[PDB]
Amino acid sequence: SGLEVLFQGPMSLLTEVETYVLSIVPSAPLKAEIAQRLEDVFAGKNTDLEVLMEWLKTRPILSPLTKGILGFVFTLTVPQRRRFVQNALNGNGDPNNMDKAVKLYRKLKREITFHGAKEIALSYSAGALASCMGLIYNRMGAVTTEVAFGLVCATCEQIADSQ
């Protein structure tokens, strides 16, 4: 309880992440399963990343981009690269998104905080943001965990804003 209040900052960051991530998951019976999986992963419950990823890969309804974002989130928290995640994490439907993703990636390597990263990321399109997530998925240690989460939240915000 006394200890518990000191950890409210990081727990509230995790609540914001799960809220953003769930906002891009279709309102289907499957959504309950994703929520309970995200809850268990954010609670530090023992998880096999390969089992989670195989389950993600074979889910119907989910768009490859939602699978990519969920794939990225699970990789960031559960202590390798999956092709379905790499393929999804892009904005190749606009050649200019790679140009912008590289420039955002350069800036994110300099950030430390979740809010600093989320604030910078929100100046970019959903397409550029997803391509930037793809760049980090290839080199996860290029940015801090808080910065990677800020980027995920910014990406979810821009996808939810277009749908």
Image (cartoon, rainbow, N blue to C red):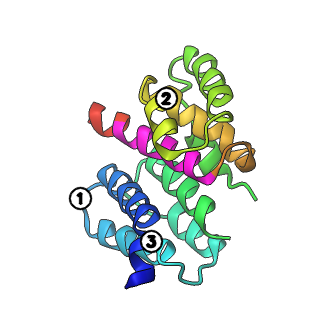
Tag of residue 138: none
List x then y, in percent, for residue 22: 33, 57
Q: Position of residue 132 (x, y in %)?
A: 59, 33
125 vs 134: above or below: above
Of the numbered discs 3 and 2, the one sitting upstream in the chain is 3
Q: Which mark is residue 27?
A: 1
Direction from residue 45 to residue 162 in the image, left or right: left
The circle on residue 120 is 2
Which numbered disc, 2 or 1, marks the residue that appears first in the sequence?
1
Q: Is residue 134 above or below residue 102?
A: below
Outermost residue to the left: 27
For label 1, the crowd category at 10 Å Cα-Cα, with few meaning under 14, some 14 to 19 and many 20 or more, is: few
* Residue at screen point 54% across, 44% down: 113
Q: Which residues are magenta?
A: 145-157
List the residue tagged with mark 3: 6
Give the class, few, some or many, for how many residues have Cα within 10 Å of label 3's Cα (few <14, many ≥20): few
**What's the distance in space between the residues labelled 3 and 2, CA to CA?**
27 Å
Identify the residue at horizontal 58%, vertical 16% (top origin): 95
Which quarter shows the N terminus?
bottom left
In the rendered structure, which disc, 1 or 3, sits on the residue that comes first in sequence?
Answer: 3
Report how far apart the C-alphas of labels 2 and 1 lie in the structure.
29 Å
- Does the magenta run of residues contain 152? yes
